[PDB]
Length: 158
Image 1 (cartoon, rainbow, N blue to C red):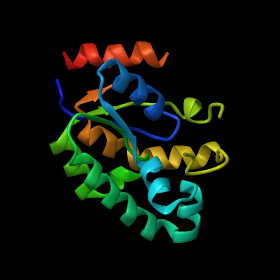
Image 2: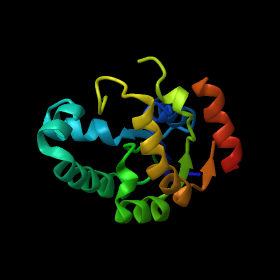
Image 3: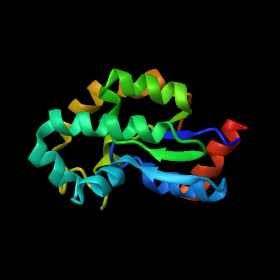
């Protein structure tokens, strides 16, 4: 259907790669909230994070996501920590089908907008997952090459 598809999960989950494939196979618009932030600030997303601090970044991100989710027929790759906001999570759930790309710590560490230039120690990623995994799972309607995964998701939505 035309219904929105929102991809959630940690950085390195393939939100952008899988989302672009989904958008092309379903002939929909693709958006990346990190990319929209860069577009509105004219700067690297990680730079905006570092300069504005968490508080300011999260507010800006929440506003960006509120606006994107109001669109129709789009595939959205949401920021990894965008699920921290309760309002955002309720908006994501209500405005489209939420697909959670469950990702191991290993995959997250794995090889190449970038919120952070370099990978952190495993401990940091484990700590993040303990806080965020329950958030991703709370709003997931569907839990999971990009082409293969994209069609699998599609088969699940069917």
